[PDB]
Amino acid sequence: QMDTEEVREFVGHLERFKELLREEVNSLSNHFHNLESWRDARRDKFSEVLDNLKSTFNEFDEAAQEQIAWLKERIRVLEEDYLE
Amino acid sequence: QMDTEEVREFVGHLERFKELLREEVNSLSNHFHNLESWRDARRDKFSEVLDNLKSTFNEFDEAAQEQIAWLKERIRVLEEDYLEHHH
């Protein structure tokens, strides 16, 4: 008894969120790796912070994709049931 | 040793990223909490996943905030040292 249009828009949001953040963290990571003139203990510490963010992203990407997969199928089931 | 323009441009990117991350997670969370019709154990689980995502992003935000401040101040100090070396 979900409102499947309501849920469809959230699914789309979650997909775009994952896509955008992947591209933005990849861009930031590439820039950081290319940054030649910052080399000290604080740079090393920040490298770990960025590693942790990537790990966090991956964990969330997995959790989100599993919800997306389920929600898209549930929307189909419910809409089919509603029409039939 | 820093090329201050190279570092400044990284700082700018980090600042933009930090602010995008905050805005995007808030938008996602607010949308999720505005959903009226998804109510089940999967929703409950995802609510905690989202709360924890925000928590982790807040950790990153503070770490990024402090790195930005340190780098900006280091640039200032290095620029003033350069000027002093010519005094």
Image (cartoon, coloured by chain):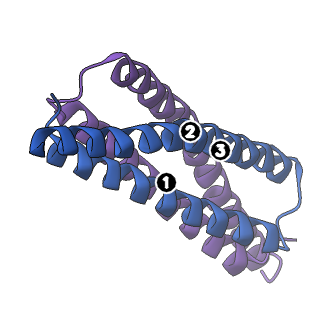
Chain colours: A blue, B purple
* Residue at the image point whose x is 23% and y is 31% from the top: B33
Residue at image coords 82%, 65%: A38
Q: Is residue A54 above or below residue B4?
A: above
Residue B4 in the image: state x and y as whole percent.
71, 75
Residue wearing tag 1: A18
For marks 1 and 3, give the CA distance. 10 Å
Q: Is residue A55 left or right of residue B21?
A: right
Choose top left, top right, bottom left or bottom right for residue A40.
Answer: bottom right
Label 1 element class: helix
Could you say which is closer to the camera, residue A4 or residue A12?
A: A4
What x and y, as percent, mark residue B74?
A: 70, 59
Marks 3,2: beta carbons within 8 A: yes
Q: Nearer the viewer, residue B74 or A34?
A: A34
Check disc 3 and report the residue beneath it: A58
Q: CA distance from mark 3 to mark 2?
A: 5 Å
Q: Tell me if mark 1 has few (under 14), some (14-19) or many (20+) residues whose alpha carbon lies within 10 angstroms of its own.
A: some
- Name the quarter where the C terminus of chain B is drawn: bottom right
